[PDB]
Length: 210
Length: 213
Image (cartoon, rainbow over all chains, first blue to last red; front, side, top):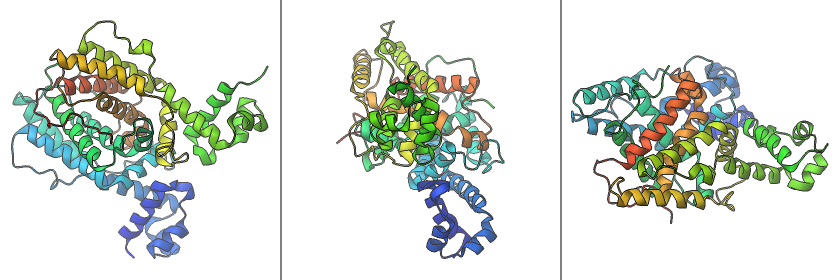
């Protein structure tokens, strides 16, 4: 068994049962790696749990290869970024539930802790793209790469997270084929309309600040 | 001096949204509420009965009233702005109701997806469908967007601020729940919805983004 194999089995259990119910013996039985050797690479159970959160962030982060586009047109460039990001959320729902587990029960108290990953990658490629479109007169000022990413993540995560309550209240399964395509369309059309809007906005240079 | 059904429902909703169904104990709810564990079983039946009553309460706390839904200025754009800000405000005022519903969406304690609806949300949908219909005929809004599409877009932003606050603060150093960012998330919800409805960009021949068979 490899380090990536144990990390995959552990991520699935933590995203389904939580930190309390997911047992190391159950992970050792499925992974094939002894509980003693799991402690050697990942450390204690909380050490393995934080590795799963770092993996969850990594699984949801698109590569520069997945976001490359020859077409200089900033509109089609942003479309590629949105669809690339959204696709990873569709392919990794276990990574989404993994991060949502931490956001509900703060098992790792991650908010006041060391960053899980260096996300200066997808932000830099998007900031440059928004900068080119703004000077070309294609996009309006006041929107940062972090604002665009938050808008994409909000839609991509809501599909997986609020699936059960939406299906109960409105009879809509956001995770079926048709609705997974519709949520992608909503993410693309919402972002592009937001960037190319002629409506009057606040004198603020960003929606989210740090 | 006597505890009420609404009082026990409030204490129970807070524990379930923080600790979950497993850790939140009836003895802890009885100690805070003042109502005996025996009398809590009399009104709510069992612990799962009390849990489902908390989910039903969580939905009505995030449902804006008809008074908040009434648009004063008869403008399609300003009318939608009032709906977006009214919905977003209830999410800001009731983060415990948001975590309550997210508890069910993660661990399906009440298997709510294949169960009786928690609340009749058809009244809020019928009013927004009328406002989008008036704006579409007035040439203000584009076709292909339903009230359910608009509500999903508002909820996505309003919920993300709460349910993804800790990871965002760790990865990007941004507290979406602080004053400045709570205003920015509201601005994003308003500007995003209005831009989406008034977009001149080419869209699919589909009459809705989300569908229901």
